[PDB]
């Protein structure tokens, strides 16, 4: 009766709480570094 | 042979690599179409054709 509030309507950054399993989805913060490796078939020669 | 006047050279990209790594563009004015013999007068750069 008197639990008061929740997290689904109080989390910061506008990210949705769910359950089973507990998780916070689509939660905007920070930066993600990307490290790549590419083959020579992806590029194109200068001549064409 | 066709006549070529008002010849200007521009360089698009360069990269001193073992293969052919630079592109050159010639702008000119001609009276009729045909063939010319391109050449480079110094060994600093080698043409392909």
Image: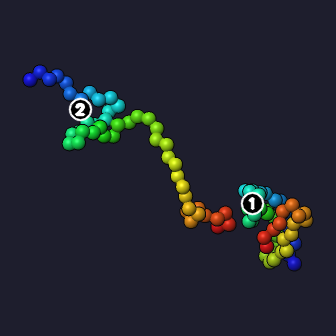
Q: Residue at x 81, y 64 (%)?
A: B28
> Which quadrant of the view contains residue B20?
bottom right
Relative image position of residue A30 (x, y in whole percent):
44, 35
Dot 2: element: loop
Dot 1: element: loop
Image quadrant holding the C terminus of chain A, namely: bottom right
Left or right: B6 in relation to B23: right
Left or right: A2 in relation to B49: left
Q: Chain of mark 2?
A: A
Residue occupied by mark 2: A8
Residues packed near mark 1 inside 10 Å, few (<14), some (14 to 19) or many (20 plus): few
Q: Residue at x 78, y 70 (%)?
A: B48
> Which quadrant of the view contains residue B24?
bottom right
Given residues B45 and B25, the one toward you in this image is B45
Residue occupied by mark 1: B17
**Furthest residue in direction front, as rendered:** A21
A34 is higher (above) or lower (below) than A5:
below
Left or right: B6 in relation to B12: right
Residue B6 in sight: no
Given residues B25 and B28, the one toward you in this image is B25
Residue A33 in sight: yes
Given residues B8 and B49, the one toward you in this image is B49
Between the residue at mark 2 and the residue at mark 1, the CA separation in whole angstroms equals: 59 Å
Q: Residue at x 75, y 63 (%)?
A: B18
A4 is higher (above) or lower (below) than A44:
above
Relative image position of residue B34 (x, y in whole percent):
80, 77
Q: How many marks?
A: 2
**Furthest residue in direction left, as rendered:** A1
């Amino acid at each position: 009766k008197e639990k008061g509030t929740a997290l689904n309507t109080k989390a910061p950054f506008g990210c949705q709480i769910k359950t089973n399993p507990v998780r916070a989805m689509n939660c905007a913060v920070g930066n993600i570094p990307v490290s790549m490796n590419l083959p020579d078939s992806a590029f194109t020669r200068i001549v064409e | 042979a066709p006549t070529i006047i008002d010849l200007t050279c521009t360089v698009a990209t360069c990269t001193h690599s073992s293969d052919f790594g630079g592109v050159l563009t010639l702008t000119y004015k001609t009276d009729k179409n045909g063939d010319c013999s391109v050449h480079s007068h110094s060994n600093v750069a080698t043409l392909q054709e």
